[PDB]
Length: 46
Ligand SMILES: [Zn+2]
Image (cartoon, rainbow, N blue to C red; front, side):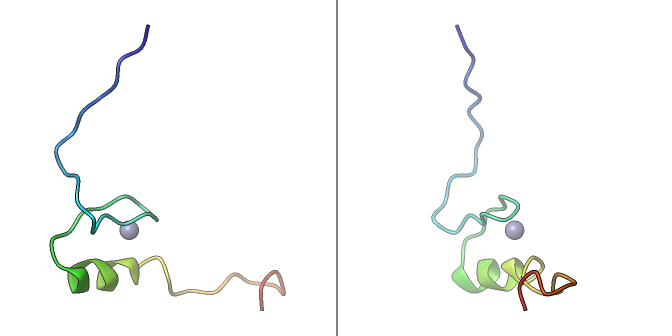
């Protein structure tokens, strides 16, 4: 058998990088910024 946890915070504005939840798009998009910023050293991407 298994146990499935059930938390409270399911919204269409939930981030994927970390897994945060918001109410307004802006609040979310702006948050995602924390993830999208610094660049990976080396030509890995470029
Ligand atoms: Zn996030």
